[PDB]
Image: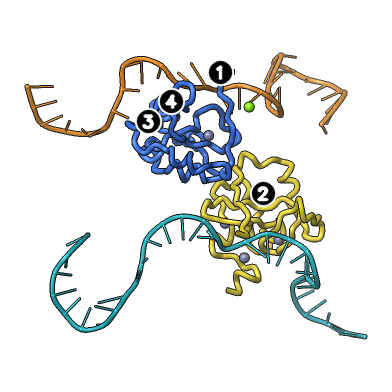
Chain colours: A yellow, B blue, C orange, D cyan
DNA sequence: CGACGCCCTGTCGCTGAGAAGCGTTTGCGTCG
DNA sequence: CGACGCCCTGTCGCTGAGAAGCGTTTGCGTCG
């Protein structure tokens, strides 16, 4: 099985530090293969704070989106998503427009 | 100080023997003050397998529910709860309907 | 943010805290 | 609902599964 565990983070567990770590420009990202996380949209594994899909039926990391990708491709802000207890990722909503999802 | 330590139990540590020891009928429970565990709902201390709340902010035994109580009062199966890495107890979800939690 | 002056002389953050289980305890309804 | 007889001898439900991220990767139009 190649699927990573999907751990839902409660909104109360979101801290002001990781809010400040939401990426505001894709060129400022820091890459780390060990401590980083992959945005589903741009497919870059970086250390900036990314979204957490809170649908229990979700799986893997398809719910992780960086700052620039979420706003530019879906008009949503990562800060709002992290504080929405009912937030679902675009793949869970069937609206993902990444190069793979819109191809199929 | 009067509160029993709450230890979050990883899903990978759940054994088939524990799943088999889930109570299917409250009349079949085995009481033991030393080796048993208390269900928050029915407040009986018995040896059957009970749920483990995985909310870090949880405490004590409020997250421990027996098989009959979880399905009859919440429509959930202890086996599913033990294998759910995001499972929170009804008191953590604020939906507990035991005689104490609905009293206030 | 923090000294500054004003009158009504003042207050929040963090940590770790926040029971458990024995006793009197088990659904519904007609009935003696 | 399930045997029962019929001819065309038969099929669905759950479970757990359903990637992730490095490499070749970043919008538009102009114009040399
Ligand atoms: Mg105490
Ligand atoms: Mg503690
Ligand atoms: Zn991205
Ligand atoms: Zn999702
Ligand atoms: Zn996609
Ligand atoms: Zn119980
Ligand atoms: Zn809990
Ligand atoms: Zn309760």
Q: Identify the subunit bearing mark 3.
A: B
- Asked where in the image residue D2 lies, by quadrant, the reply is bottom left
Assign a secondary structure to mark 4: strand
Nearer to us: label 2 or label 4: 4
Structural crowding at the residue carrying mark 1, measured as other residues with C-alpha within 10 Å and reported as few (<14), some (14–19) or many (≥20): few
Q: For the point 78% across and 58% down, which residue is it?
A: A25
Q: For the point 37% across and 30% down, which residue is it?
A: B29
- In screen coordinates, is D31 left or right of A74? right
Residue A79 image label? 2
Q: CA distance from mark 4 to mark 1?
A: 17 Å
Callout 3 and callout 2 share a chain = no
Callout 4 and callout 1 share a chain = yes
Q: In the rendered image of this protein, does residue A60 appear above or below residue B3?
A: below
Residue picked out by circle 4: B45
Q: For the point 69% across and 52% down, which residue is it?
A: A50
| Mark earlier in primary sequence (4, 3) | 3
Assign a secondary structure to mark 1: loop
Nearer to us: label 2 or label 1: 1
Q: CA distance from mark 4 to mark 3?
A: 9 Å
Residue picked out by circle 1: B2
Structural crowding at the residue carrying mark 3, measured as other residues with C-alpha within 10 Å and reported as few (<14), some (14–19) or many (≥20): some
In the rendered image, the quadrant that contains the N terminus of chain B is top right
Circles 3 and 2: CB atoms closer than 8 Å: no
Callout 2 and callout 4 share a chain = no
- Relative to the observer, which residue lies in front, B12 or B74? B12
- In screen coordinates, is B99 left or right of A75? left
**Residue B104 seen in the figure:** no
**For the residue with label 1, is its CB less than 8 Å from the closest atom of ligand 1?**
yes
- Residue B53: x, y in percent? 53, 36
Q: Identify the subunit bearing mark 2.
A: A
Residue B29 image label? 3
């Amino acid at each position: 099985s190649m699927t990573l565990p999907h751990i839902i983070r409660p909104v109360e567990e979101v801290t002001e530090e990781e809010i400040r770590n939401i990426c505001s420009n894709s060129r400022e990202k820091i890459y780390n293969r060990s401590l980083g996380s992959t945005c589903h949209q741009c497919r870059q594994k970086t250390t900036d704070t990314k979204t957490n899909c809170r649908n229990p039926d979700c799986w893997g990391i398809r719910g992780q989106f960086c700052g620039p990708c979420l706003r530019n491709r879906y008009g949503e802000e990562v800060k709002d998503a992290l504080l929405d207890p009912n937030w679902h990722c675009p793949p869970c909503r069937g609206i993902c427009n990444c190069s793979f999802c819109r191809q199929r």
